[PDB]
Image (cartoon, rainbow over all chains, first blue to last red; front, top):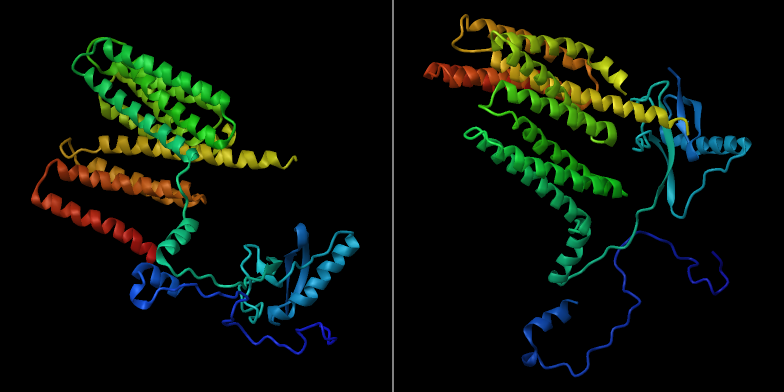
Length: 49
Length: 405
């Protein structure tokens, strides 16, 4: 490890394991139907996903 | 008692004798021990041990199982003269994986834990079904002759034998891998059964003593001839040769002249008794330079396993035929069976191989059980069945108890 600015890991220490937010960036689905217009099968599929 | 000398296995196979501290905990030794084996490899001119990515160094038994890092060498059942292995065990830490929609999730996981049917297995199943078919065909053909011993049975069976054998011939010449050989072997094994009844079905007139002699002869010859040229499936072929040869002698005697079955049965029993004593000697005589030792060891073991098995079949068939609930002093053969069973039960402990030791042990128990059943079905009575049932259930329970307790 180096302190010279480009090394972002300096001063960071591992304490264990757990959850973290992935590097993915989700875009909201366009023209989403209103709650009464949603089909039941595809609704929970996209929601739990 | 302060130290113990043991062999340590290292990279690529070098065994080194070391004198270890008998009471320090094993985790304290693995670091300097690794240095020592590396230093010796360097002086020997070999390449040292090295790590690969993420992992750790551990000390294990020859079976690879690692020793508990905190326990003393004396706390574990490690004695002077034993051997251990130093090994690198890689890091298993990795992300967890989750699939939420259940239909996909069932398919994905279920497809990784089991094997789907494929063309290689399909062929073996086909071979297995045809073998099962012909043994049924010969069975029905062999049953017809008892009512009409005409030429039909032999004429019909002979052509099948030739045809199956002709197919097996092309398969044997073409085989390239062990999968191919298994297919061919199952086919060849099945060819012996039709040819046997085909020959035995040739002598005309009512079936009996004269027909039997040809069958067991050709059976013994066919089983023996296959082994000579094939060199595979030693156990199954060998067992047939023994039972065939012995029956040929017995059949010949009965056909020529024999006052009683007891006479022949007693003779066979004695022949097996002496054979049981000679068994290991027969196996020894029947069987880059290192390879020669490995081949001989399993071959000898194979022949012995079939030999012990075949004799077992003969004595159980003979003993169950010798004892009888109506003939004379009914108790005399029953006690003789007991003495015979004890010898086999006692001698079975002298064999280290599981199948050799287990088959011998099982042979004695089945003899006892068969006699109990014999004296129960015939000369039937409420007390007789009652008495036999109690004995037959407690007999094995006692054997299990002697080993379990």
